[PDB]
Image (cartoon, rainbow, N blue to C red; front, side, top):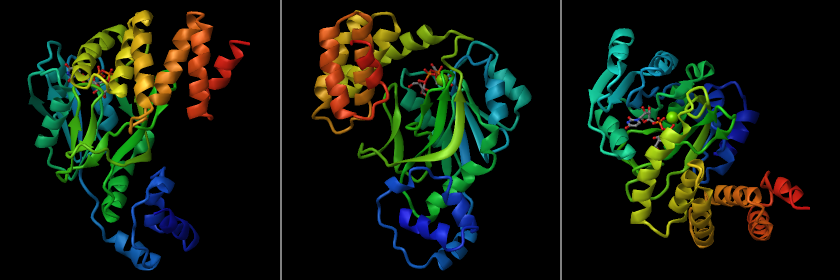
Length: 333
Ligand SMILES: O=c1ccn([C@@H]2O[C@H](COP(=O)(O)OP(=O)(O)O[C@@H]3O[C@H](CO)[C@H](O)[C@@H](O)[C@H]3O)[C@@H](O)[C@H]2O)c(=O)[nH]1
Ligand SMILES: [Mg+2]
């Protein structure tokens, strides 16, 4: 696909196929074989491709303070919006009924499984594609019209993937493994009680297309200082995930992270050490760098320089471009 793009850029770069493909960020990374044939019939053929429909799904519990700004941010850009309420005790449903009558409201007991609630929306959705957003997110106005173009180009090339907008924390931390959107063609389901993500039902990990969409995330802003509250909820769920895979370094990391967020640094260090130990021979090393960086932060703060040296050396070996290595090195000499 990077080849096809290089020629679409060269050979006349004002085709609607050119623009729309440029919404995709990590094109260089997509390695499945697309039979390059002739950019001419490809350009022309795109013009007649169908513009897929997209459902926007929101799972909600007690979001009175936020749901209106959230829905105002998505009200223009989706064929269908489904809100799945877990029997809120605040006035969440009534705000939606009043100000967003075209939103479909469905109800479902919370079962302490974020993947169950999301998959419930997938069952209810009638569009060709789904995109999930949370009540403490804002969909950027600059996204106007783009999410359907993304889905159009992906259907065109029959790319099986999930789709990640950039999500910006209040901190300015920018995430690109967010996996919020995918085609509703019976291939992808959410898996996990917490920290859930959409998996092929053989439980393999879909390719992740990063796209030039932006979503703001207010949910850990000190405006609402919900930090410790959301954290205690998630750690009870992370603990269940860990029981089922007590050697999984990803779950060990998330548990350590949440112990740390709950001012339990002692207790975090042991889980992070075991996570880092188990990551060496693990296939999905996505959070290996975050485990190392967090552990080095904790050891540094506790003046445990001897152990900090051990993990900083591992950090720099595995991730020589890590932007945090120089900081730790400067703090101990
Ligand atoms: O019992 C609940 C709790 C939460 N939500 C909704 O789930 C969403 C995400 O919950 P949130 O308050 O934002 O916790 P966060 O810590 O900000 O992250 C979230 O952590 C969750 C669990 O992994 C989410 O699914 C992820 O999208 C992640 O961004 C919200 O729209 C909530 O209203 C429910 O529907 N029912
Ligand atoms: Mg949130």
